[PDB]
Length: 284
Image (tube, rainbow, N blue to C red; front, top):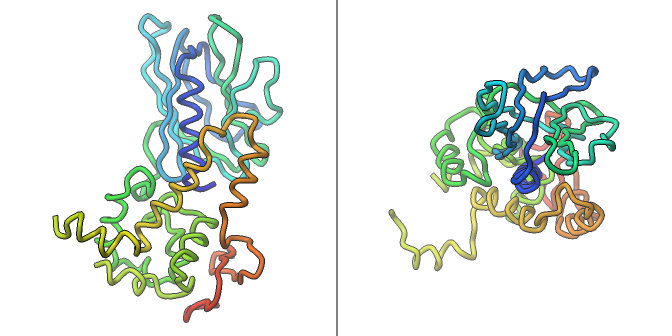
């Protein structure tokens, strides 16, 4: 998955669980190789936040809840088929590998992490993955400063289409985003990364920026604004029944990835990069 989805998923959990009270233990399917979640509370609230391609759930016991339980955070990585779904207790999805059940007050429901392929993972604790940089959606300024400050890193000797997938610097950018981003600026996917960013190495006022930056956004600005477009398009459809409608809108939003006429190549990782025109000097 890519940044927009994790963000939208987090929004869904928070909104759906805002007034729900969960209780009991957190159940993991026997088949799941992920860790068991030591937790038990008669009444707790679930909240979530996202950062790049990671979603963090926080389980917070309500006052009076028993037995004594400290808040617990869990960080998830969705994988190809992972998702969060809120369903009726008697309709648990066949591939629900981690489940949280609502407490007696009101209709019995279950928040589930569903993942048929089981590529998804979760770890105990609220610590984000070591080395992942700032989220391109929620931490734009920190994301940008970190890239410019570390341009000397060997990560930028690779072609731009490959560096865009390096989560140490572009946390949240995935295969369809790098294609759409590069297409907006018509930047050859195999141009040396540092070469495309070098020029970017309380200065300009708003009037100056409006005159020379507004209609000429740079690669780093788009790493934030492009995925933000997907977030706006997605609205509050995650977790609902508007899946068909949402994918149709996403399909229409794409300008390059998997589009007719567009060229395609395989990077050193085997991932397909879509582009239009010149592939670049470092093309395989």
